[PDB]
Image: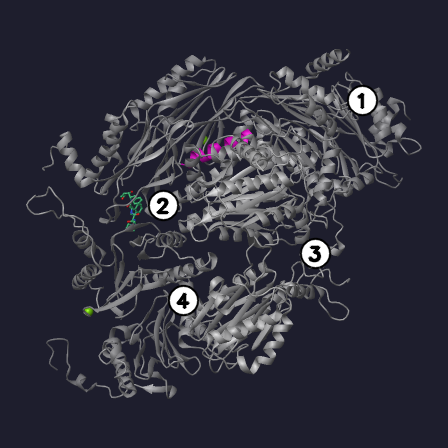
Amino acid sequence: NNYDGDTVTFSPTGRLFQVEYALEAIKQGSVTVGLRSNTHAVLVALKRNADELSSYQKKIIKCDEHMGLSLAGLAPDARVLSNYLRQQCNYSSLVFNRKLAVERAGHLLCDKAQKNTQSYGGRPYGVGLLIIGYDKSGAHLLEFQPSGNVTELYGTAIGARSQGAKTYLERTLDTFIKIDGNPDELIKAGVEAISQSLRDESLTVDNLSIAIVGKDTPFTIYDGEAVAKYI
Amino acid sequence: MDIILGIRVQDSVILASSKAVTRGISVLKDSDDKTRQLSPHTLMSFAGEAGDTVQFAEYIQANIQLYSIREDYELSPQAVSSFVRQELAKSIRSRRPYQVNVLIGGYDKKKNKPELYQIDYLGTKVELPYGAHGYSGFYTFSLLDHHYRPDMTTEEGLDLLKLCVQELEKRMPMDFKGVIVKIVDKDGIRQVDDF
Amino acid sequence: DRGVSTFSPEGRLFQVEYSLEAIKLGSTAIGIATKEGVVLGVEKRATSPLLESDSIEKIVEIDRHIGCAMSGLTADARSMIEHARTAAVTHNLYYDEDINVESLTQSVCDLALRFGELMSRPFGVALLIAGHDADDGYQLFHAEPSGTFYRYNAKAIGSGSEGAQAELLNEWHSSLTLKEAELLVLKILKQVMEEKLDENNAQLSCITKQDGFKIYDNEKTAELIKELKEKEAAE
Amino acid sequence: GYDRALSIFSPDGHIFQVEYALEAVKRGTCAVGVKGKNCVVLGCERRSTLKLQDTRITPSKVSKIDSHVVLSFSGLNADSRILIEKARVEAQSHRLTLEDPVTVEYLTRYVAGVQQRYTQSGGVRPFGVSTLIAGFDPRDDEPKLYQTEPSGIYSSWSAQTIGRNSKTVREFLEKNYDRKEPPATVEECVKLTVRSLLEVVQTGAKNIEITVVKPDSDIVALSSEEINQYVTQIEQEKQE
Amino acid sequence: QFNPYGDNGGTILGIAGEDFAVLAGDTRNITDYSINSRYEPKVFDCGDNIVMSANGFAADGDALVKRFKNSVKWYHFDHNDKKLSINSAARNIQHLLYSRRFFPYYVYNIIAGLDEDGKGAVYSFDPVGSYQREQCRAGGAAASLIMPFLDNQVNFKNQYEPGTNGKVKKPLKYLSVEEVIKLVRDSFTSATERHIQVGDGLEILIVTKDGVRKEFYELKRD
Amino acid sequence: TTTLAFKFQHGVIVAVDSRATAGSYISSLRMNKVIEINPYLLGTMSGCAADCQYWERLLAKECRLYYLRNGERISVSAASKLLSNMMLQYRGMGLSMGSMICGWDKKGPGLYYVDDNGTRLSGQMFSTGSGNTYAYGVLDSNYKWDLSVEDALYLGKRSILAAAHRDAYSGGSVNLYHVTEDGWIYHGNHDVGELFWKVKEEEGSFNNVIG
Amino acid sequence: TQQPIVTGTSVISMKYDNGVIIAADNLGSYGSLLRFNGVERLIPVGDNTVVGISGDISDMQHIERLLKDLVTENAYDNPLADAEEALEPSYIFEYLATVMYQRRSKMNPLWNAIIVAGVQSNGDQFLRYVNLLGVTYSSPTLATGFGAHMANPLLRKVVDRESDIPKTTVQVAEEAIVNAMRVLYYRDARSSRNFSLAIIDKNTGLTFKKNLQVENMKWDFAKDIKGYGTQKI
Amino acid sequence: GSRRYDSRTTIFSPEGRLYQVEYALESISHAGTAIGIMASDGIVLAAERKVTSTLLEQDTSTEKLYKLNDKIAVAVAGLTADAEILINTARIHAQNYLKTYNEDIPVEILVRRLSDIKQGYTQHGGLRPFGVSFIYAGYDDRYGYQLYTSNPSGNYTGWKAISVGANTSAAQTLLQMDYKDDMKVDDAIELALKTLSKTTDSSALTYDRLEFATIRKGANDGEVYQKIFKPQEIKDILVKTGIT
Ligand SMILES: *[C@@](C)(CO)[C@](*)(O)[C@H](Cc1ccccc1)NC(=O)[C@H](Cc1c[nH]c2ccccc12)NC(=O)[C@@H](C)NC(=O)CN1CCOCC1
Ligand SMILES: [Mg+2]
Ligand SMILES: [Mg+2]
């Protein structure tokens, strides 16, 4: 109200409204789902178009051979943050000959987002990210919020109507975690999960976007007729 | 570059400058004009290190032309020469000084007098009836000391200038490929096409 | 007052949303992509008859294989065009090749959100970036001040955009020829324009693989206008 | 440093600071530009509220940017000096780096760019100035006349006016100026420029300034008596 | 006084076939009269069907290769996983080298692969960035030993057709990959004999449309 | 190297050798020392190969940007000046470059010499490189404005040959160009080895050499 | 640009079937003065890596601190710091190599020659060299300074190529290293009798031996040597 | 943050005016009147000190008339402290020109420079403008005797006669009436004092409430002399013209 003019101002109840408004941008964004087993990690994203003449906005970005994310909210902010991750993954490889741990990647995103919430002039990031990866401690899935909060999860979903997919994963927890050494079945579970967040529209060939990473699988994105198999 | 001469007569200033440009052991050009018009009644000839000369001259030309447009007024030769001197005096203590020597020949329309200024790369300014830079003065100043009068005509000034070039052509080991001569008077700047 | 980079309660940047309103006031620009080329057309909209219309430059070359049309506060586009031209030629310097239309568009859109308290406000202009490369063929992009860019088969921006976009919705198909696309831009421009469309107050352009980006002459466009009139009168 | 964003968008998609700068231009004295077949004439209004003025030394309304290009304006006088200085510096900077004088179109594009930059830079306000830029490109006999404004947009004009009561003189020019046959001579071009100012000026004494620019850097400013002869001839024909 | 440069020896060789290319180099690394390693790889697969070797000062060589491999990675990120063509890689490397015009990478660089028409391609660089496409090139310590041999046995220089006596040249018939590898092996065996910094091992990288293949051969260890 | 270029009635001829050296070792037998900046602009190369390639390819970028901004080809005079200004930024930093910017513009055919010192000279005829003195000898005695395109191409070709013969650091092959108002025209790569024997027989020159 | 003041001499090392061995004497020389006699030049990093350093001791102590700080930094927000995400020899080396090359590129080098010896997660042997120029190389045997000239020849007789590594036992490898250290004591004027030796095995882990002495030295034959040519008494 | 407290000194009003410049001009209208009159053979500068005290040391006091160099002087109207900041800058600018070109700075060039500094404070920086209006009286060999004025907007104009400060409307009307082109310095002195005597808010115009100065070619042969009048000399010229 009087305490939402900038990010540097706490409300009387200890809330940061600009951060909460940035969180709101994520809820307006299109749905995306993340889930993992012990061998593989999968991202599934519902792409959004402007109209019938337009293309479908890309949702998934590659950060390294072993790491990538899906976005929901302001796409340019995802480009800035994914660029930062690319650089950090790359710094770890060039200097230490070491693939960046997914947990550490999350800690770096948290700290970068945090600086924008405590300083005058700037603004919080208006995007939420689901980071998947495979490192020395196996498969991982992270959820990033522009408040700074980063959370390691078995599965999750963000965006509009994301609660439906999140409930499904909460039921299926014991099943999909055990899907080891079977990428197609893990993607199926993800496609079935994101389907719980659909209304009116359904999953078409140029609508659906899928990405996967695992033990002997580099981060690869599937679009177009490559996802027709899963429709 | 090498030889640049100047002489101030009754009603004009005459500048003579060599045409040769050398690179390595080869004369690349024998028609080079080592001068820039700073204003309608002010001419500057130059000589020094390769590249620095033209860059400095054009930089000065741009500054004087800028002043002329801003004030709708031509600076006096004296004012121009002082500006040039300061730029060179500023330059000599820089990281990389500009190694350029100049003669500024101008006709002051206010005083109705020709004026010749000699400025070296250190910023050493002197007003003279006749001047030169480098080794040029070693050969020519004795002739000028002898023959020069302040009431000389432009034609007589050219004849005395021919005699100076003939002496240079005889006693210098250097082939400078003749000179381009330019006259600065009340009517402006013109080039003597046959010399 | 309030921050320039402030979020609204709905999760939108106030300034970005307000710049979009400025673009709605701009003159109409239309782009149509085909397999034979991409056509770009604009409404010139001279404020007075004494204004020499040929000086109105709302269609612009970025490279030989990339063209651009603008709508909104057209003065804001000059630095965007300058950056685009620099990016296009710089990539040619670094990689000895033409730059991808998408990559060029992405470079322009990176400028968009570089504002705060960098420039003091977002751009007040939208761009239709049309071009061709070997990888993805003939392409048409719509670059906004939000930093977002969508690819389009056909797109209209400016004051008559939503009316033109609905018309493009019906008319566009994947087998359109270049000649058909030219007449289609002229048709839709003539529809949404206030004044009567002629060769002096409207401008056409195209990008083909062979000839590259070309702005059409007034004599060439005049014939296409006369060809349009006759074919509409044919039924 | 002072970084405050002064020029910003409003809910309806307007930049008020840029629009208020146009109001400063509206307040400024009238300036007019007319191009003939082989010349361009720049007319300027001088408000007669200020007498006891020294016309020798008072800043003239038309300013030479180079020997072949001139610039007149309407709006804040102090703001116009900054643009003129920058333009003059750029004109010499172009000659120095490219070895050709600026084209009229290039000089206009630069001045317009400066005006635009001051609409999306922190800590600064827009120029309260619109300019008319006229001249002839080097080794070209085609007349050139451009206009700029605070937003940074620019365009070419057969004839144009800016400043206070510009709406009226533009009305006059739109009906009197024929594109198929423009003022063939200098006389006809000046006559039309004076006529257009006489619609607004008040008295035709020291209130009208005229500057004729011809090809090949031939720029002259008319005197009071020369202009007064045009004023006399116009009204004598009008008495009929 | 500190000397930031050093010489790690070695020699490299690139040959462009009709539909293939090879980049070979010895595996010996040295300082002065000592051997550091008998097997220290010098020719690298940089991705996109491009091989590269920066011969001279190993620290600068490793840094340049590392930076180009990085340049390939960022080319994929920035331009939608587009394949970096050999000509584009060459121009990119020029700019990497010239960025240190006033403190140069002390290396002679060669890359090899296939052009956009599928034909064999070899590009050669000097330490400051001048480059050019070629058919044949030896670089490094024994470069002057090997190049004349290749002018003779690859481009048939100073060879004419018997009977004509200098009137008709030997026609420039193309070479197979098996024929090229023979010339490479003989080139390095000969260089090993007369150059003290060449020996230990030979590693050859062969590039075809099918990918990048490796072949290793022992060399004299003295 | 040896490079030359000269103006004449039908435009400008441009001829260069193709040798590259690293000390006494011939590093390259065939290196291109001409750059096609645009269909109406050429640039010759002499000195440090790296410097020549980098700065002339950067000139092309800047010349290309000129066309996009102004919708018109850059003049030869302006292009040469941009290059000389680049050289003036790295004043005394050790750059080694000597080039001739050759082209056709509105003023007709244009030819400018530019070097690492910043020197910029307009002229009818120029020659750069270690073998420039040998080329000048042939050019000065046989040059006319009234030359035919055929005879002019031969003169530039023959002048490089003279230098390639005598100068140890010049040779390999001759690259010929002819600049017209419709643009430049490539007139091929000519091996000096073969060209020498051909010229010797047909012309009767090089009598002292046995063949 | 500087000059080395207090220096450490040769560092020698080799691979064997199950791991690597590395050794270096305990001397800190000040030119020709044998100034400091209790200097440790082998520095363990965790339980899987030993970094051996020769050259300037002040720069060695600086590197020693960088490594100590590297371990501290790796443990930050890292639950697997003593397991899967522990520091590897390859990580430690590449870090140092990056630092060395950067410092030489600023014309302000760390005046050292370094050998990083260890065993990776997968049991693979790691042995790589880096110096003040940023030059890196790997080999079955590695040695710095005088060791390169005298030790390598002896160690290469045991492991001449890659295929000899599985055939070499820890007892044979240690014996070769200890003999090399004796030879260096005979012939290097800037060396000492006292030295340290470290063994990093994939089975038995890190064994760090201190206060070792060169023994079984041959000097008796010196009594018979008289004069420099013609002298008999 | 800090934005909350920013007055925004450099913005347009909806009518296209600069708020702070207009308000600065309002400040200046309360300042003591200063008058400049240009004649064929010289220039007069007359100014009124504001409500003084008997205990003010007048002979060592200076609040209105300042010397920029030997050829150019200024009369001040507004904040004195603000004026001194600008005056010292102008003094330096004149010496920079003299050092560079070895000639005394032309009057207009000096005026333009100061006016450009004032202009800058209205367009950028976020600082308040200088609350000062100058009358420049000077001489050079190009245009001879010259009068200029500048105000906080940074706009400057040339004049035959001009007033700044309080009651300029009334003062300008009186000057416009009695001024003629063939006028001389002695006549201009009388006109300046008569105008102040009629426009003043004080009961009577006395020597202790005035600062006065002339720029005359009335110096021995072709040269110019600046005369800053002393208290006793102002008292004498008041008696001579018949005011006291
Ligand atoms: C004569 C041959 C002079 O020797 C020419 O000027 C020639 C000019 C030239 C220009 C562009 C491309 C090729 C050649 N210059 C050289 O060949 C030049 C001579 C040279 C060598 N060091 C120099 C230092 C300062 C000035 C000139 C120098 N040679 C080079 O620049 C060498 C280092 N470059 C190459 O040999 C280029 N290599 C690229 C990879 O392929 C093999 C050749
Ligand atoms: Mg001197
Ligand atoms: Mg040996």
Residue under numbered circle 4:
G100
Residue at disc 1, secondary structure? helix
Q: Visible in this render: residue G88? A: yes
Chain bearing mark 1: H
The stretch of residues the image draws in magenta is B51-65
- Residue G168 location in percent, x, y? 26, 84
Side of H69 relative to E18 (left or right): right
Residue located at (72% from left, 22% from top): D197
- Based on the displayed image, in which of its 4 quarters is residue A202 positioned? bottom right
Chain bearing mark 2: F
Find out if the beta carbon at label 2 lies less than 8 Å from the nearest ligand 1 atom: yes
Residue under numbered circle 1:
H188
Residue at disc 4, secondary structure? helix
Between the residue at mark 3 and the residue at mark 1, the CA separation in whole angstroms equals: 58 Å
Contact? badges 4 and 3 (CB < 8 Å): no
Asked whether residue B97 is drawn in magenta, I would say: no
User: Residue placed farthest to the right in the image?
Assistant: H203
The reply to whether label 2 and label 1 mark residues of one chain is no
Residue at disc 2, secondary structure? helix
Residue under numbered circle 3:
C3
Q: Visible in this render: residue E109? A: no
